[PDB]
Amino acid sequence: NNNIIKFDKARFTVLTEHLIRIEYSETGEFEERMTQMVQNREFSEVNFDIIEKEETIEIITSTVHLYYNGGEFTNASLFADVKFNFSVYSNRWYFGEKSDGNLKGTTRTLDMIDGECPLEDGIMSKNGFAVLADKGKVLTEVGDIAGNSVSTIDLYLFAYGRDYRQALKDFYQLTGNTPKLPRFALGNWWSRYYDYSDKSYLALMDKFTDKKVPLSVSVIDMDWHKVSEVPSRFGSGWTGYSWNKKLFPNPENFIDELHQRKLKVTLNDHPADGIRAFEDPYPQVAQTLDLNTELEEAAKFDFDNLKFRKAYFEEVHGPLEKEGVDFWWIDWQQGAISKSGVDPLWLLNHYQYQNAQKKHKNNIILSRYAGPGSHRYPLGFSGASVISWASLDFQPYFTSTASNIGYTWWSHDIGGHMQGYKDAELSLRWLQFGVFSPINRLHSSKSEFTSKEPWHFDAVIEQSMIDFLQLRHQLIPYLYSANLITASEGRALVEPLYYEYPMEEEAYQHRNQYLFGEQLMVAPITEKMNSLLQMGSVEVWFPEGTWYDFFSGQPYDGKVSLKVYREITEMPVFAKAGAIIPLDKNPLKKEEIPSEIIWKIFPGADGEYLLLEEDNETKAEFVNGIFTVTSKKESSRKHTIIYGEHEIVSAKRGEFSIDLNGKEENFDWNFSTALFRRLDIAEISYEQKDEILQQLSLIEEHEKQVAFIKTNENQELQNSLFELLYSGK
Amino acid sequence: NNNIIKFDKARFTVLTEHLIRIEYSETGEFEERMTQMVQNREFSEVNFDIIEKEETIEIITSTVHLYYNGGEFTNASLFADVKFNFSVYSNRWYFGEKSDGNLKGTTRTLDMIDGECPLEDGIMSKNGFAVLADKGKVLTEVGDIAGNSVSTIDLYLFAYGRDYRQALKDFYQLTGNTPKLPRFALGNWWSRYYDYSDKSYLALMDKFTDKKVPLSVSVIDMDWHKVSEVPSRFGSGWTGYSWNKKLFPNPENFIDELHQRKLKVTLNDHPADGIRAFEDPYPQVAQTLDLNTELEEAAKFDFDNLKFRKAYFEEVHGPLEKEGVDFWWIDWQQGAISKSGVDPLWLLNHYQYQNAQKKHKNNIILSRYAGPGSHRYPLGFSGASVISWASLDFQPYFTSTASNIGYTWWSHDIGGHMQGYKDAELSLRWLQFGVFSPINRLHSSKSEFTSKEPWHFDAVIEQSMIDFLQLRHQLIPYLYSANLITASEGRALVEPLYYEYPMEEEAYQHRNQYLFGEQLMVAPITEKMNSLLQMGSVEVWFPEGTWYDFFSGQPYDGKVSLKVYREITEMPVFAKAGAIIPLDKNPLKKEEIPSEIIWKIFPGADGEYLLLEEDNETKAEFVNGIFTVTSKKESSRKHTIIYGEHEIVSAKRGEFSIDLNGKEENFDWNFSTALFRRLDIAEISYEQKDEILQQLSLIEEHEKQVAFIKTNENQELQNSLFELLYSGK
Ligand SMILES: OC[C@H]1O[C@H](O[C@@H]2[C@@H](O)[C@@H](O[C@@H]3[C@@H](O)[C@@H](O[C@@H]4[C@@H](O)[C@@H](O)O[C@H](CO)[C@H]4O)O[C@H](CO)[C@H]3O)O[C@H](CO)[C@H]2O)[C@H](O)[C@@H](O)[C@@H]1O
Ligand SMILES: OC[C@H]1O[C@H](O[C@@H]2[C@@H](O)[C@@H](O[C@@H]3[C@@H](O)[C@@H](O[C@@H]4[C@@H](O)[C@@H](O)O[C@H](CO)[C@H]4O)O[C@H](CO)[C@H]3O)O[C@H](CO)[C@H]2O)[C@H](O)[C@@H](O)[C@@H]1O
């Protein structure tokens, strides 16, 4: 190709104006095969310039000067200057050195993490460049490990500046796009490390129904298999492939009962102790792998071994899939050691994801992160977080930052996994976040005390949790459409603010704030409430424009940074003027696709929403106050329109238009009602409540209402009253 | 042997069902010679199974699967699964990797340590396996360094599960048993970094006699030799081999005076500056080593050099031994550097211990720990601890944990060495521990203010220290018998609780609690007293059974964890129902073996004690209330019997039996007396003392006495009163 340049023992491939592959080969042979990370090096031709001399070469694109002075790659021989001024003297890459600016990526797991842990770098940098080293093995055409690359150094220089979305799109072109998820993955999951019977598990699923809590997924954790019943001469019961017949005397019948309730079923698999002589599948595996059964030779875990993988999928997983298991929860915690040098977690995710496609279309796994490119094997499983406010306060930042290495389907244990402390408010705040996260999977530890069942908690917490769990199912149309946009266009569901606002310093100063699809901006509360206010809070950055609370219609004039206060039952979620959000009207109704959509419209601007579905596309347009709905294919779907406060159209079939210029634009939300509510719940003196209500009612000029609250001895009460005054300005 | 298997470049020796030697050789030659660590690879034949294929081998014992996949040893090629379920997924060893569970061992020294320091691993693990790498040089048949092993990797896989005692016994079979100590080592030692004269040292020894404090050992620290008198052109006076003639004008006469007082004599040796031209032995050493005397060439320390070692033992130590020095205090702090790569401390301990056997039977050294196997060279010398509560609080744990690498004769500076802070209670608590430690050596810094003389302190502290120092000599029969059991049976004097109680979680949660021989359980107090109670405390775990305070007879019903309180003059030491403890009746009497033994019997169960001595064995049996004493050889020894409270038999000669079924079983200890004493010393309100005494006297039901103390505003006073109520239940 003209986009390929050799010089000395190096090869440079200009993939885009902003993406250069850099290779070294001692043998003069360079690597064309795919790697664990890289699936495609076919990119459209681009323009660039070369200055080639006897001893040096310079490659010049629109955004980078790449220099190579010959010899072995060192910090002195291989380096690059970006054509940006984001920093005064951090604009140079040196081979093998770190520079400032990296916005980070993700890490394998949150196992045993109480609050923050270090993250690996991603491809995004405030200074406009990042290097992604390809240290993986080569693949065969069909995707097996083939051994060591002939490019003994193989790097990708990203020089996208602050065009983060294009960097991620081209990363997906290089490493392969995320596959489409199935719609069932986006609903509520039930999980608990608890020794249920068939009977008690079905009773709990029927209790969810009775309690008006929708579920898509039934997880069965490790007590599905033999645990205490494993003879100690075999080691532990952690690994198992044999049903506990006391708890599950007829597994296929039990899975049939979950399938009748329209649940997908996954089992915990701890693979590390392989298939030992006590297991139900051992006689078949022993025959296939020529094991010495009289010496009870174990089929040890070896995902480098083709015969072991086949016996694992066909003879261990196969019989359980035949009983009705839909997909695998790969729960690997036993290290990164293999003879090949390939991480066993990568071998599991790669081969299990491929194998899951045999029995179900667009099937998933649930497994820990296995390095760049492992987004090809959703879903991410973050693991055994400590139950704490600190863990919750880390998790929104963790989730949005992961988009910077393309790993956009993290499933966290909602409410935290293990250890830590009881606080029903922490559980409720964690579920609020979960509902506005990639995946909403309730899960917990082997404690008698850590169930995430809403009715574990008091009547107030229970009702709020049920409301949020129903909201998750209302959001499935929006989530599923965003899922198809991840798969087809390389856009993350969850974006850091700086994807949309790369030049706004405040977009880098609100770690836990994020965009959730294209219509919603989320600022989860992740700190225990101030007991004097009976409200939690978060500092929200409002970009330029008019914003509304998604739930209340409270307005906010951007651009501003403003501390916002919510009761424990309420979450800060915002939509711009012109936002259109579809909701399932019937979130409890078991049906493959919604028979009714609510179109929720935020007044004050034009807007547009495209609802992508399995077998349709539906466009909602809001232009000069006219709302139009069209679809590619006709259906019997009934549309409901909510314009600000008011239901305008109820259950209307087919394509249509309706003029909303005549209809009431304003939400009900008002300063006086909100003021009364905040004062009434506050654990402060009644004389202070009386004086604030009287003075804020009497004082007419906005600037003098603000001067009055500025005198308040309660600093946080000032900020809460200021939020109401700012919204009422 | 059938217990030897070769595969690829590896050799496996199945020494026991639970102990496998693992070797790699590039040359096809494997090492048969002893090493610094290993003295014996002769073990009885055991059964095991092999699965040998073209490319892999598996060795199977009762407790482990050892796997080798060929090639160089890596974490992927060499690994093992234990046949235990102590953990869920920590049951696998990977070559070159650490696993969880190791119960730790010991370290070189406590020099400069204020409280805790890190320890090396031992051979004991809660998860049931440990690997002991042999990185040492090979020895010749006579025990000189021979150079590098031909087994370039040489490992010992221990897979004993929680059979800790058998692991230690087989460790001693591999590395050699601890030698027998001489009886004199088990008495009190006097030491102080102080510039005594012959006259002032003998005056102090005569003051110990006048004060009723028995001593076995007189240590003379470095001011025995020239210090300030060394010309600075030679360096410091730290190393010296020349008596300071002002302080010791006739050394042999002074050592004769200590020998007449039945004291063994040791001198401090700082070897690192060798024999310089100012030293008294230099002319002889210079002649032997062909040194240039006109250029004052030093005989530099070089324990790799046979001629240097001979001149050191024969011409430097020899003349001092001829003046009467009994054994050497090797005080090495100058690093681990030698041309051979052997630690100079190991060369000193190995060669000096061997050389000490020439002039005295079962002789000792006193030196720092020199790695696994250095238990062959007792005694351990922990060195320059900081004088602090933190240092004392670490030291029982330090001492019992050392049994996990077989190093069972640690001698700590009792009361701490240097720096730190004055607190007479810390000195007293430290001496209590010392008396129930392997060796009771009083030692201190060059301060005018740090003498460990009991009469340094007030009358209360002095009398308590004298009482504990007399108790050490009462315990010499018990210590000496346990010493012969260490030497012959590989059982440590000091055991962690988990040796006796491996499956009790509480045996891992009382770091400072230990078994002291087979009849006593010690819980030293290592925290400053609560001034409101005038008592210190420690949480004691009482195993199943009936336990008695060794001193008071206070009873405790196991199994329970219970906070116990003692005045600063009293130490928590416990014996089970049926315990028999021999004591010297005449601890001040100078005699090679006791002319009278007290047999102290704890009622309520059968018991047995075997008193091993230099030239006898005496068995005390307590069966169905009959006490019998028999001996292998007749003697004129007089036996005293104390059954619980009461002396039954006084000074009875020969073998005999006596029925104690008719005699009073109960100790005097009673709730009311103990209650009055605790209230009386407490620095609390008299109205609280009055109310507690009155209410606990009046309230009859035990559960209501406990309910009354539960209302007390003083939390620690509750726990102290609860201990009395628990003992009185
Ligand atoms: O010759 C000038 C000066 O250089 C050396 O000291 C520097 C020091 O004064 C200071 O300078 C920074 C600038 O680097 C520039 O930084 C911005 C930063 O403020 C922020 O806006 O973010 C951008 C983007 O990331 C930065 O690049 O301007 C600011 C003022 O706002 C100056 O403070 O810091 C740098 C880095 O530590 C120093 O190199 C020199 O030592 C000194 O003697 C001299 O006067
Ligand atoms: O599939 C189950 C679970 O596995 C992963 O998370 C684990 C996490 O739930 C937790 O589990 C432990 C168990 O490991 C077991 O541990 C005991 C320990 O309690 C104690 O008794 O001492 C023994 C001996 O040393 C341990 O082996 O049982 C306890 C309950 O008492 C569980 O808490 O901790 C481990 C280790 O961190 C996790 O691997 C998985 O991430 C999770 O999603 C899943 O539900």
Image (cartoon, coloured by chain):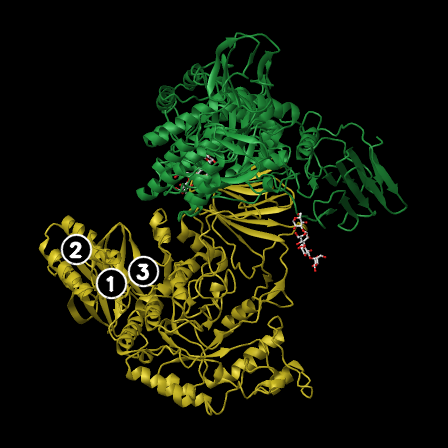
Chain colours: A green, B yellow
Q: Which disc number belongs to residue B728?
A: 2
Give, as a three-letter code, the residue at label 2.
Gly
Q: Which residue is mark 3?
A: B523
The correct choice, above or below, for B712 with respect to A91 in the image is below
Say above or below: A644 vs B544.
above
Circles 1 and 3: CB atoms closer than 8 Å: no
Q: CA distance from mark 1 to mark 3?
A: 12 Å
The image position of residue A430, as x and y in percent, is: 45, 35
Closer mark to the observer between disc 2 and disc 1: 2
Q: Are marks 2 and 1 in contact (CB under 8 Å)?
A: no
SS at circle 2: loop
Q: Are marks 2 and 3 on the same chain?
A: yes
| Circle 3 residues within 10 Å: few <14, some 14–19, many ≥20 | many
**Mark pair 2, 3: CA separation:** 20 Å
Q: In the visual, does A359 lie left or right of B554? A: right
Judge whether residue A242 can be spotted in this image.
no
Quarter of the figure with residue B424: bottom left
Query: Where residue A629 sits in the image (x, y, percent)?
Result: 58, 13
> Image check: A371 left or right of A196?
right
Q: Position of residue B269 (x, y in %)?
A: 51, 78
The quarter holding residue B712 reads bottom left
Which residue is at the front of the view, B80 or B710? Answer: B710
Please tell me how crowded label 2 is: few (under 14), some (14-19), or many (20+) other residues with Cα within 10 Å: some
Find out whether the residues at labels 2 and 3 contact each other: C-beta distance under 8 Å: no
Residue type of the residue flagged with mark 3: Ala
Tell me the number on the disc at residue B550. Answer: 1
Instruction: Provide the chain ID for the residue under circle 1.
Output: B
Image spot of residue A397 (x, y percent): 54, 39
Answer whether residue B193 is visible to the viewer in this image: yes
Foreground tag (1 vs 3) = 3
- Mark before the other along the chain sequence, 2 or 3: 3
